[PDB]
Length: 143
Length: 23
Ligand SMILES: [Zn+2]
Ligand SMILES: [Zn+2]
Ligand SMILES: [Zn+2]
Image (cartoon, rainbow over all chains, first blue to last red; front, top):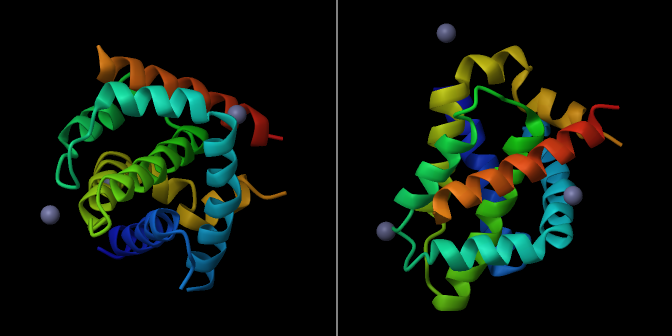
């Protein structure tokens, strides 16, 4: 599954660098750049709401992603799919990834990243392909 | 419920962003 692999790589690298706080094909790099610009912006603009959501969710640990999965599934339960919701999901994923680091230094952000990727790729695979995948993602948020 | 509330927030912020970039 190439789409899954690419998605997991992109999403993982963003969450990891957001969590640790530092940065270490072409499409993947452009997507990560777009994700950095839009995703950081979403986190800054909606920190209060994100904080509240996080507090209410009360995530204990890195492996505690089941509630998050239910939330991502429910987001699309109205039958609406768009890039805006997708990037906001990933943004919140990074916000959560940071907090886990607050709770402990050594958390693997992988379970969180894979949790997000599974919902996107499994449930919206044909939507993603129709939208031109991550190339479509980059184009949509272009400035 | 926290999950539903989270979903609605993400749905609201997502749609805001989508409308914004939709040109
Ligand atoms: Zn906003
Ligand atoms: Zn684990
Ligand atoms: Zn198909």
